[PDB]
Length: 281
Ligand SMILES: CCCCC/C=C\C/C=C\CCCCCCCC(=O)O
Ligand code: NA
Image (cartoon, rainbow, N blue to C red; front, side, top):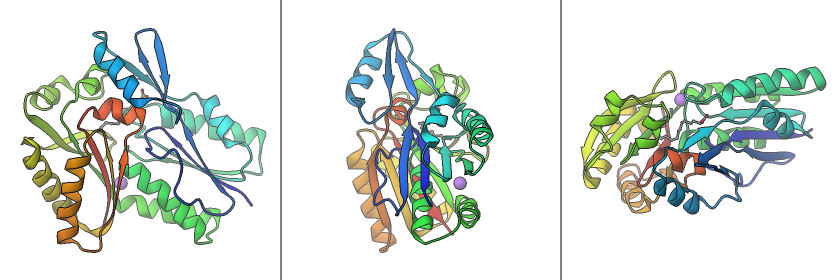
C-alpha cells in the first residue's frame, strides 16, 4: 500500500516535511535556459548562480515544462499517486501530467492517479502538498483523499508581491499592459492567482512598508482567519519576518512557514519576490 505525492518545481519543497508512512515525495523539475546553458530545477541547482547568469545575460531567458516521460518516470513504485502541477494556464506542466496519467494507466492498470491543477504556484502548491500528506497520515483511502483535497483547494489562495516582473513579460505570461505599471521604479505588484490561474493585479504599492501593509490588508480582505500560511520568497526574508509578526500579532494562532523559492519560482518572481499561500474560511 504505497503512495507518491508528485509536484513540479513550481512547488518549493525539495523534501516534504515528515512524510507519511508508505509515502514518497518527488519533485519534477522544469528547466530554465540562459543562452546556450540549461539549468535543471532540481535540488542540485545552485539557484544563486542561475539567477546571476540570467541577470547578466542581455538575451532573454526562457522556461520549459516537464516532458510526459519525466512524469512517467516519477510514477514508478507507487500504487496511489497524486500529482500537483503549477497553473496549467501559464505552463504546459499540467498538460504533460494529464497525458502521463493516461499513458501510465495503459501500462499499469492497478494504479490510481489524481492530477491536480493548482491554478497557482509557490506557497499555495506547497500547502496543497502538505495537506495531501496530512490526509494520508490521517488514514484516508485514495478516493477519500481526492475528495478532501478538492475541497481543501477551495480553501486555499495565493497572494504575491513582485518588485520585478520582467521575466514574466519576456516569456509571455504577463501583458505589457499590466507589466509596465508595476515592477518599475519603486512599484511592486501586489496580486493574486486568478480563478483561471493567471496573474491578477490587486494593488500597486510604492515601497516596502507599503508592500507589507498591502499584503496584510489583502489577506484580511480575502478572509484569512488564523490558518496556515506558506511564504515562498526570493531574498525577501526581512519583509517576510515583518509580515509574519504583524499577522501573528493579529491572529495569535497563525501557523506560518517561510521557504526559499525554487529555481523556477525564483526566476519568475525575481529578486525581492514573494509568493504567499494561505488558508481561508
Ligand atoms: C498563477 C500563479 C501566479 C504567480 C505569480 C507570481 C510569481 C510568478 C512565479 C512563478 C509562477 C511562474 C508561472 C509560469 C511558469 C512557466 C513554466 C514553463 O515554462 O512552462
Ligand atoms: Na485555490
